[PDB]
Image (cartoon, rainbow, N blue to C red):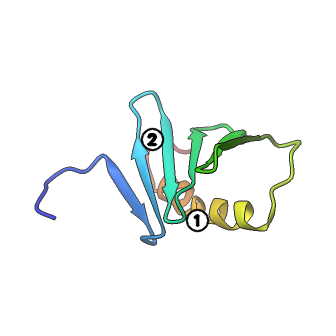
Amino acid sequence: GSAQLLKSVFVKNVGWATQLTSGAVWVQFNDGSQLVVQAGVSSISYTSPNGQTTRYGENEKLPDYIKQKLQCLSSILLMFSNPTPNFH
């Protein structure tokens, strides 16, 4: 793809993440499901294309597949661990 700047990021090419200016990251996976994550927040919103959105909070348990896909988001957290004044 011939493009300079991309506002979407592909994780492992298993999922696609859209960067929102409000600090929200929308990550869709290849299985057709989508996840909404807020920066700095552990409570995420998972949407399944069967018409089922479930909200995960720190007081909520993920099923196997949900935890599995959530694991891939760790890469973005590590990307924020890059030596920057916004990191401590």
Q: Position of residue 65 (x, y in %)?
A: 72, 66
Q: Please report the residue visible at 62 percent of the width from the left and 38 percent of the height from the top.
A: 40
Q: Which residue is mark 1?
A: 72
Q: CA distance from mark 2 to mark 1?
A: 25 Å
Residue 73's image quarter? bottom right
Q: Please report the residue visible at 86 percent of the width from the left and 52 percent of the height from the top.
A: 61
Number of other residues with Cα within 10 Å of mark 2, as a class: few under 14, some 14 to 19, many 20 or more: few
Residue 77's image quarter? bottom right
Q: Which residue is mark 2?
A: 85
Q: Position of residue 56 (x, y in %)?
A: 76, 43
Q: Are marks 2 and 1 in contact (CB under 8 Å)?
A: no
- Judged from this view, the residue extending furthest toward the front is 50
Give the left or right position of residue 61, taking residue 43 as reference. right
Q: Position of residue 24 (x, y in %)?
A: 50, 35
Q: Give the amino acid at mark 2.
A: Pro
Residue 53's image quarter? top right
Number of other residues with Cα within 10 Å of mark 1, as a class: few under 14, some 14 to 19, many 20 or more: some
Helix, strand or loop status at disc 2: loop
In this orientation, which residue lies closer to the viewer: 32 or 61? 32
Label for residue 64?
Answer: none
Q: Of callouts 2 and 1, which one flags the residue occurring earlier in the amino acid sequence?
A: 1
Q: Please report the residue visible at 30 percent of the width from the left and 46 percent of the height from the top.
A: 7
